[PDB]
Amino acid sequence: KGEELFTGVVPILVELDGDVNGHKFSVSGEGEGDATYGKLTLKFICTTGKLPVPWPTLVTTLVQCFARYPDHMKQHDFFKSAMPEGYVQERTIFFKDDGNYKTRAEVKFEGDTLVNRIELKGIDFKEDGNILGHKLEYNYFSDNVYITADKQKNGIKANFKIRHNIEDGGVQLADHYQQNTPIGDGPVLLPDNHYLSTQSKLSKDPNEKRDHMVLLEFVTAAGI
Image (cartoon, rainbow, N blue to C red):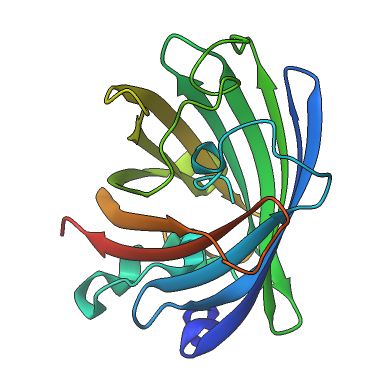
């Protein structure tokens, strides 16, 4: 029944309030998702002026209910099974040799629109690190979200790493720890171990003068 909400193109709204080492900011996003093709097209705007962290570090926080689950893996799709009431997605993101993000989001339908409401808290960041010093490249990254069942919370856990390219040629590692719990008390699909292969391509609207990010993302379930 949750899965039936995702058979076509769904409009998406994202709203994030963030505080990183006392720098407060807000991000608003709009776009659409097509889970048939695991395809997300979004545009994000920093509504408070200039973003105090690199756009790439926010991509993972800024809707895995749009993953393409192959037919033979459809019994493992927790994300869609929690809809429309939705789920809470929580993360800790450990930036190697730097600070950490803690995120809490509620992902749910408001009418026909899939809404992701986020609060992000960043602490222990270095003033001259890769994040607050804006030393990360703005291009493309890809990795696997390793998902396991969490039966006690009727939800899932996930772990993955993002290797953010640094401008000097190095790598800024971000270790992601994730938990998802349903908002409703209906039955949800608790999956076998598997992963989401995710590719994120970042670009700029040549006509947009506000601090912004255009995102083309593909998310595909695999490993069964």
